[PDB]
């Protein structure tokens, strides 16, 4: 009963959507670990079709998409600019409003009104007198905040109490004390008085500031005591961001969904590439499987021998099963980027298969050698350096999840990027790139104009910024490892080689699990693990289970008995 507000708000038909010009495949269902429960999010299989008949509509949608990050979620930065070049990760998010029944048109009213969110002002008594009387419809299911209290953060009103009114005693702990008199004993010096003393009051509920719902926030919440501190608010003492509150509360989950889809697209592309490369386009290609999650990974706190299924599906393809996006993305998600799952479980299977395949290849290829050199070469093959060198050229590591997704300081917004001029100076001046510090990035104060209609800083401001950058040479900022704070700005990353060495094996692991050893063997040739001889096709496919013998295992005589 202290959580049904989202439970119904999340279940509102009025939703939002993501708008693209390139199409999408089917995507895996995702879980969300909210601070009040668990959520599941899916992407519609069939997108809607809209043509941009007016460039003004496109510009307004872009402005609203930027405004959401700038104000609603507090993601903006002084250097942030709406991207106009539109090459690197450019797209938009558009809300929906229930149109002609099955149609959910764009909330054109919302974009036309809230180009920018209004500012909660400390309205005084004098102007409150002639201001219009608050209406119950004007506040129901909307967004409000307390301009009088130091808690300036936006908050949400759930239901309106027309029967309640000021001068009403607090039902809990203050039966002798009224809301009205408490207001003066708390903020009377700041409000002056409450006008329209006989009107209704509203019941409000707070909003979380947390933006990463991947991990289960296990703890003794004490939900009954969580909402025990109940708030009833006077309408005229609080601002009103008149807004479909359900859409707002859904918008907090947006960055996590965006990041998970961003990486799941890489997973899907890898699945397509590896399915095609092994000539796998049979019936199990279609559809998708909902993404699973593990429990025994610590931080996710909340007769006759059985036939071995892997061998059975290796020899009998009736038991084969299709790999899915979840497994590949799990093999992509590094431990450092501690999501609900990670790549560590498939790593052991991949390591074992790589060891066995290298051993078999060496034995069936170099049978004229002793054990010492064979073991030495085998350990050289499965060594971390070799795996790193053979996976970098595979061009995979740019599509790896290796850093924790914290949006405010370790993320770049989708539709927002750095100014084009400073980027062009940055990516073409290696002598100057290494000296740029985050203080220099925050030196420029780019207002609405630069981000909206310009995309670049002014020439005088350009000179000021570059002078501030060059002044770092004589200060402590010189010689600092700024890549810790600028790589995510320039779309760069630093990754330990252990991650690459383990993630190659993690990739091999799911392939082994789903299909069988014989099909998995070709992937070593794909990563040029073993320069397989075309003269014997089965050596890279099956002869590893069929070869290895010579004259020293063939002679027949009962004398050996």
Image (cartoon, helix red, strand yellow):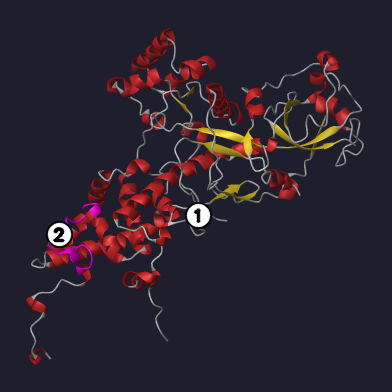
* Image side of residue 511 versus residue 184, left or right: left
Indicate the position of residue 543 as horizontal and vertical percent values: 19, 69
Indicate the position of residue 195 as horizontal and vertical percent values: 87, 21
**Viewer-side label of 2, 1:** 2
Above/below status of 17 relative to 527: above
Q: How many residues crowd mark 2 within 10 Å: few (<14), some (14–19), many (20+)?
A: few
Taking the spot 88% from the left edge, 35% from the top edge, the residue there is: 162
* Image side of residue 456 versus residue 56, left or right: left
Cα distance in 3D space between marks 2 and 1: 39 Å
Taking the spot 57% from the left edge, 56% from the top edge, the residue there is: 302
Residue that numbered label 2 is attached to: 534
Residue that numbered label 1 is attached to: 291
Corner quadrant of residue 372: bottom left
Predominant secondary structure, magenta span: loop
Is 73 or 67 nearer to us in this picture?
67
Q: Quadrant of the C terminus?
A: bottom left
Q: Earlier in the sequence, mark 2 or mark 1?
A: 1
Is 334 or 111 nearer to us in this picture?
111
Q: Secondary structure at mark 1?
A: loop
Taking the spot 21% from the left edge, 58% from the top edge, the residue there is: 379
Q: Which residues lie in the magenta part? A: 526-543
Residue 542 is covered by the magenta coloring = yes
Q: Secondary structure at mark 2?
A: loop
């Amino acid at each position: 009963e202290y959580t049904e507000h989202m439970y119904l708000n999340l279940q509102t038909p009025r939703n939002y959507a993501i708008l693209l010009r390139n199409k999408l495949p089917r995507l895996a269902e995702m879980p969300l670990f909210s601070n009040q429960g668990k959520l599941h999010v899916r992407v519609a299989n069939a997108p809607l079709e809209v043509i941009i008949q007016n460039s003004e509509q496109l510009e307004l949608l872009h402005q609203f998409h930027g405004m959401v990050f700038r104000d609603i979620l507090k993601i903006w930065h002084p250097f942030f600019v709406l991207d106009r070049r539109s090459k690197e990760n450019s797209y938009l998010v558009v809300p929906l409003i229930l149109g002609a029944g099955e149609q959910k048109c764009f909330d054109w009213e919302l974009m036309t009104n809230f180009r920018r969110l209004p500012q909660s002002h400390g309205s005084n008594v004098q102007q409150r007198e002639q201001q219009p009387a608050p209406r119950p419809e004007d506040f129901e299911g909307k967004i409000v905040t307390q301009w009088y209290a130091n808690y300036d953060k936006p908050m949400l009103v759930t239901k309106v109490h027309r029967e309640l009114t000021p001068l009403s005693y607090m039902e809990k702990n203050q039966q002798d004390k009224t809301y009205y008199e408490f207001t003066m004993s708390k903020y009377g010096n700041r409000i002056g008085d409450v006008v329209h003393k006989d009107k209704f009051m509203i019941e409000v509920r707070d909003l979380t500031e947390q933006l990463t719902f991947y991990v289960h926030n296990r703890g003794k919440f004490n939900a009954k005591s969580k909402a025990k501190m109940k708030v009833i608010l006077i309408p005229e003492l609080c601002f009103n961001f008149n807004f479909p509150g359900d859409l707002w509360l859904k918008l907090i989950f947006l960055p996590s969904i965006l990041n998970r889809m961003y990486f799941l697209l890489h997973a899907e592309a890898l699945r397509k590439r590896f399915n095609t490369y092994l000539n796998l386009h049979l019936l199990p290609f279609n559809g998708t499987d909902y993404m699973p999650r593990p429990l025994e990974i610590d931080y996710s706190l909340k007769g006759k021998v059985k036939p071995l299924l892997i061998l059975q599906k290796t020899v009998s393809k009736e038991h084969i099963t299709p790999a899915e996006q979840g497994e590949f993305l799990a093999a992509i998600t590094a431990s450092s980027a501690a999501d609900v799952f990670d790549m560590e479980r498939l790593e052991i299977l991949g390591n074992s298969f790589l060891k066995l395949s290298a051993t078999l290849y060496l034995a069936s290829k170099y049978s004229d050698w002793n054990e010492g050199t064979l073991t030495e070469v085998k350990s050289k093959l499965v060594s971390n350096r070799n795996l790193l060198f053979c996976l970098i050229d595979a061009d995979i590591p740019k599509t790896l999840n290796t850093i924790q997704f914290t949006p405010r300081y370790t993320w770049l917004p989708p539709g927002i990027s750095l100014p084009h001029n400073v980027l062009a100076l940055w990516r073409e001046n290696p002598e100057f790139a290494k000296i740029i510090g985050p203080h220099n990035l925050r030196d420029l104060a780019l207002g609405d104009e630069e981000s909206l209609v310009k995309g670049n800083c002014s020439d005088i401001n350009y000179n000021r910024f570059v002078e501030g950058c060059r002044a770092n040479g004589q200060s402590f900022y010189a010689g600092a490892d700024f890549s810790s704070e600028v790589n995510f700005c320039v779309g760069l990353v630093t990754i330990p080689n252990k991650v690459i060495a383990d993630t190659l094996e993690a990739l091999l692991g799911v392939i082994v699990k789903n299909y069988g050893l014989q099909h998995a063997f070709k992937m070593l040739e794909y990563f040029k693990i073993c320069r397989a001889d075309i003269d014997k096709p089965l050596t890279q496919l099956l002869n590893l289970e069929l070869g290895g013998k010579k004259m020293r295992a063939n002679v027949n005589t009962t004398e050996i008995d």
